[PDB]
Image 1 (cartoon, rainbow, N blue to C red):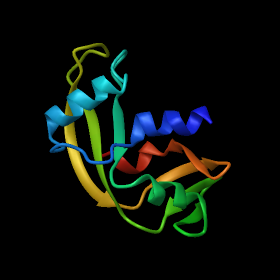
Image 2: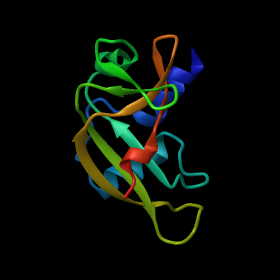
Image 3: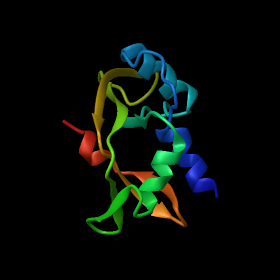
Length: 120
């Protein structure tokens, strides 16, 4: 139920506009991720079907401890906090990318994005 919805709020944007620093600064604000400033956050683009499918054999393999890694590659955008303060205004540097993603699934739905793969 709610955790999947929460996943989409935090990590899904179907048809993003641009994907530059200002894109991150705005979407991080819209999705309620700036109080306090989330240090790093990645959005997956495209359709939802392909993301849920990572939870099945259709588009995923088991990964590490109870995670799943997608077979297909996704357009993504990683927003990384810069500046000193933990509180707003939150300034973000955007990094667009294209590769597979790691999630945790529950009852066939993604409920966690593993952010470790988008650092550095």
